[PDB]
Amino acid sequence: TILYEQDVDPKVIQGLKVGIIGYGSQGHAHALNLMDSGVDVRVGLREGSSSWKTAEEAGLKVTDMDTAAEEADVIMVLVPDEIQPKVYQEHIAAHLKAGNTLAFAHGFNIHYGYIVPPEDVNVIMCAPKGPGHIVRRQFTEGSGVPDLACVQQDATGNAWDIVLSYCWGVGGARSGIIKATFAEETEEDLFGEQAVLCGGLVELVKAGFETLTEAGYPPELAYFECYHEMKMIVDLMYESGIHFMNYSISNTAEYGEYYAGPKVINEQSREAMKEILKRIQDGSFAQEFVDDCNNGHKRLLEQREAINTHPIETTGAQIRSMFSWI
Amino acid sequence: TILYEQDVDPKVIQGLKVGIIGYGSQGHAHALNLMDSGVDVRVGLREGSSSWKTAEEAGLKVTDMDTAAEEADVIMVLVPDEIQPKVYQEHIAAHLKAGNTLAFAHGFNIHYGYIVPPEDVNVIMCAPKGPGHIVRRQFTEGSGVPDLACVQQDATGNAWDIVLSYCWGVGGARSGIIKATFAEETEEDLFGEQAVLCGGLVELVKAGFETLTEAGYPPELAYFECYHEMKMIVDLMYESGIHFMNYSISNTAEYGEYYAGPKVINEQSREAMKEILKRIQDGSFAQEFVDDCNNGHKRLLEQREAINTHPIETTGAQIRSMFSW
Ligand SMILES: NC(=O)c1ccc[n+]([C@@H]2O[C@H](COP(=O)([O-])OP(=O)(O)OC[C@H]3O[C@@H](n4cnc5c(N)ncnc54)[C@H](OP(=O)(O)O)[C@@H]3O)[C@@H](O)[C@H]2O)c1
Ligand SMILES: NC(=O)c1ccc[n+]([C@@H]2O[C@H](COP(=O)([O-])OP(=O)(O)OC[C@H]3O[C@@H](n4cnc5c(N)ncnc54)[C@H](OP(=O)(O)O)[C@@H]3O)[C@@H](O)[C@H]2O)c1
Ligand SMILES: [Mg+2]
Ligand SMILES: [Mg+2]
Ligand SMILES: [Mg+2]
Ligand SMILES: [Mg+2]
């Protein structure tokens, strides 16, 4: 089920030229981890982008997107999902040669049919299960974010060797690579970020913080209890399991966990998770999201403004600004 | 509202002998952080404890609980909350002298009245807002878990100086010390662990993992998606705010966050939080917990067995054992 360093061949990606289109969250992580893994990488950007100089200063070769796509054997598309079909049609498609590989870090555009690649190129994905800044940070610390590896089209007959070697180059074989399909990855990744990692988690910490401040407790106190301490609890779970986190916390807390958890994450919460999954699988969430992107990110940005001005953020920025380290 | 190093005086706790009763999750953290901060510390344990040799090997003075309470000026009680009244009456109370300080790391027993200390001793609390192993790890890395500082009784007239200095000694001034009362700490601490940090968080990750495995996804994939990635998201929030974590994740994920969050943490979840807080404030949760403790921890241990043998735990133990670093 899970593959590690003995299951992959680093030489396969080391023998191919990689073009990373974009330099955002995933783009910088993939480009720098592959550079450090001995791969010939170049980053493709719009002329005059502010990210040009950043990438150059980090030691990477930077060129325009058309040049990166024409030079590369593996073209990895790391611009926002809603932008990829336009960037693909205008700067990538005409430069694909039979025997190149087009790669993604999410299956959204190929699964939902917004990009249809030509027949004589591989279509692969290396999807790190982790946000880009951390895909970079863990690799520099000797660890690595786990990846899902997928092949939609194998024109060379070695697409699997190529995608597994690319996961190696971004740190995935340190923690584990799982083979999956483009539809599986798209659906589980959408579900996780909606239900648990970003949707669920940020609303649970906001609701706790608002319960405490509504009840009269000071917002600095509520930040250190519901928000800052979260990292500490999750660090123990990440390293050593729920059983070790529950051994570290007091018996008072552990009884409280078992009593309160099903009350806060209730039958309705579970039914909402089933409905989240249903709208992912039926394509309705993907259409909602692309509709909002074609309406100037209207919903996204009014929701961004609301959370960025929430009292948990104003209180947290002041607290964090006063931390001192020895 | 928040106090830092310039607001505390390290020399006060450096001038007092501290006795730590117990050596569990908070106990080892307070003993070793105070040792490293230049305080004269001893740990008090039962003769023959398996923790005795671990504390000696870490370089602490270790004695029996009655000797540590007789040697000390500040006696910090870091045994489980349900057993503090018995250890206090049998090994601590008779050794308190006028001018000593009795300290706790949670206000549960003094708030709910299970311990009533004598009149000429200070009664203080330094409550780190973090699990003990991390109170120690952050201090050794040059950071520190923030603390609540409280004074229930000030016999010496300098109990505030002592508790703030003690918070300095365990790393609290690096991140912030807030003054609070014993009632406020007890209520907010019980609420946070039940509603958010331990109850809410573990059931959220369980429910996402079970949704995916019921829907046919493999458990190892559901572990990496719902459980392992959580640390990574929370790290960004801890270091740089929700606005930075939302800048790091894709626009697809950020739209997904804002659409799905209120559906999973719903109006019922919010009403359950307000009920959790009401049973904390009215003492009913405290009595429920102490009744379970007086029944052999029967409910706690059946629920511990059920989560320790959940597929999320069996899958995680096997995944984590194969990490290369
Ligand atoms: N964020 C994550 O951690 C994460 C996790 C796993 C997978 N994914 C997947 O990785 C992929 C990329 O996501 P991301 O979040 O890394 O992207 P991102 O950070 O939002 O992408 C920013 C990059 O796209 C370029 N860009 C933006 N709009 C553009 C346009 N109209 N034309 C040309 N370039 C444009 C930007 O250019 P400038 O530099 O010039 O401003 C920047 O280099 C997506 O498929 C995503 O689902 C993301
Ligand atoms: N856990 C946390 O992170 C946390 C966070 C903040 C505050 N608090 C508060 O800190 C206090 C201590 O909690 P904790 O979780 O650190 O305790 P703990 O780890 O459960 O305490 C274990 C220590 O208590 C001793 N002990 C156990 N039963 C005993 C008995 N019958 N008689 C004598 N000693 C006994 C143990 O002895 P042996 O070593 O001999 O087995 C061990 O040294 C509580 O007030 C708690 O609310 C805890
Ligand atoms: Mg993801
Ligand atoms: Mg995603
Ligand atoms: Mg606490
Ligand atoms: Mg507690």
Image (cartoon, coloured by chain):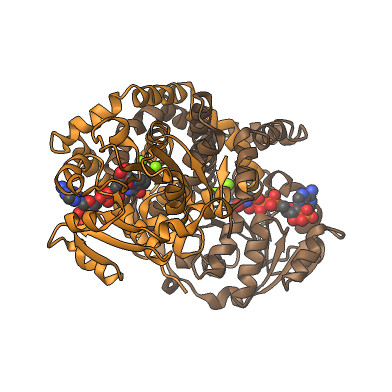
Chain colours: A orange, B brown
Q: Is residue B23 above or below residue B162?
A: above
User: In the picture, residue B61 is in which quadrant?
Assistant: bottom right
Q: Toward the viewer: A170 or A285?
A: A170
Question: Which residue occupies 55% across, 38% down?
Answer: B220
Query: Horizontally, is B74 left or right of B187 in the view?
Result: right
Question: Which residue occupies 35% across, 27% down?
Answer: A280
> Is residue B184 in view from this perspective?
yes
Query: Horizontally, is B54 left or right of B256 in the view?
Result: right
The location of residue B182, given as percent across then percent down, is: 54, 50
The location of residue B242, given as percent across then percent down, is: 33, 49
The location of residue A246, given as percent across then percent down, is: 63, 44
Question: Which residue occupies 13% across, 61% down?
Answer: A47
> Is residue B124 in view from this perspective?
no
Q: Toward the viewer: A28 or B148?
A: A28
User: In the picture, residue B165 is in which quadrant?
Assistant: bottom right
The location of residue B76, given as percent across then percent down, is: 66, 60
Count of marks, rendered view: 0
Q: Is residue B17 above or below residue A69?
A: below
Could you tell me which quadrant the N terminus of chain B lies in?
bottom left
Could you tell me which quadrant the C terminus of chain B lies in?
bottom right
Q: Toward the viewer: B87 or B174?
A: B174
The quadrant where ligand 3 appears is top left
Q: Is residue B211 above or below residue A17?
A: above
